[PDB]
Length: 392
Ligand SMILES: CO[C@H]1C[C@H](O[C@H]2[C@H](C)[C@@H](O[C@@H]3O[C@H](C)C[C@H](N(C)C)[C@H]3O)[C@@H](C)C[C@]3(CO3)C(=O)[C@H](C)[C@@H](O)[C@@H](C)[C@@H](C)OC(=O)[C@@H]2C)O[C@@H](C)[C@@H]1O
Ligand SMILES: O=c1ccn([C@@H]2O[C@H](COP(=O)(O)OP(=O)(O)O)[C@@H](O)[C@H]2O)c(=O)[nH]1
Image 1 (cartoon, protein in one colour):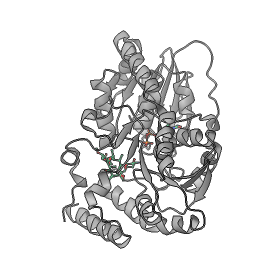
Image 2 (tube, protein in one colour):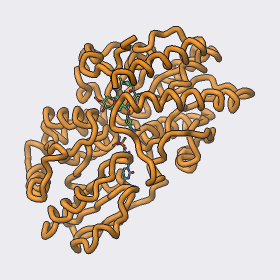
Image 3 (cartoon, rainbow, N blue to C red):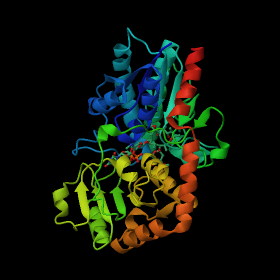
Image 4 (spheres, protein in one colour):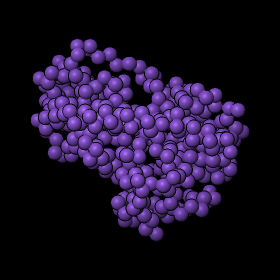
């Protein structure tokens, strides 16, 4: 019997993209899927087969170059709280006459447990990044409730007030980091201390789907190796870095696709070498199916798309989460890590050439690609959700 499954997410490609393979699988299985997101993402969600439930957000739009995310967790958590306050009633109104049978929610979609409780329906977290392992709060002490110093006190005070007002008695830190049930969009082997993560998490590897909505990328079709350079969907405002990349690839016998993000006008790079094409935004997944190397910020989505395609990486992280991902890449022998303020043209060139030609890296990428093929993906995730629906 078809059920109504609602996805709650936040307006960022790194949070939305992994969910879409699960949407596509659920729709294929005959379920009615609705998807709470902003207008910016409605067309993409529609293409996946879901009905958008559009809400108004105060979060920085990845399409608006006049605003950006903060780099620090403290500020970001404040933003997600204020957004939760404002989004909660919008979703309650939208679903008033048509409550879902189950909610699948992103790590930052804090209205979900509130409404799951209110509506007495199951709610399952979908994590696009690594989850809390044994001792997590010591490594990431911003999640510890102290009740920048004043800022964290103010945040926890306000978070506790929100939760209590809306009938959630879960202690604040637990609310933030310990979901009752979570489907994780990476394999356990990549997860930091994955062996210490308990059975309320299931690691299914990347869950991205058919991204035909983005269309195809047409390569030169000359047999030359293709390098993708892309720093994700958020922390991309790095003109000097992109100029350094141009110098790095000049005279390289490779085709290069350079994605510069929404903050940088491609014309501000000037004349680019003849082997380079520059865009603000590219069909990254399609290009990664054709690529021989990838200069990446090591966001989890980008990491998992590359690994699914056995593409070696040179990681230049922006925020701490990405540094942790880059360290895992190094530890697993899948690429190189060059910290942001240690980048030069020569270093980038040497790294790309080294990772793309290393037979040991190639062997390890082949192994990891197979692990991902075995992890279960969107099929396993949909199975888990259907098991919950069978009871609910
Ligand atoms: C290890 O250091 C990390 C720790 C933490 O990295 C986060 C995450 C990924 C950040 O999101 C990112 O925030 C930046 C600002 C924008 C970005 N994009 C939308 C563009 C977004 O994905 C958070 C702020 C989002 C958030 C609200 O759910 C939380 O803070 C919660 C309570 C969170 O701690 C738990 C679920 C634990 C188990 O997960 C994590 O610690 C991940 C790894 O915050 C990062 C800023 C630090 O770099
Ligand atoms: O030009 C681009 C740049 C990024 N992406 C997609 O945006 C997502 C970025 O997510 P990630 O987790 O790597 O990083 P974040 O944007 O969260 O920092 C991935 O799915 C990419 O395929 C894309 O399609 N085209």
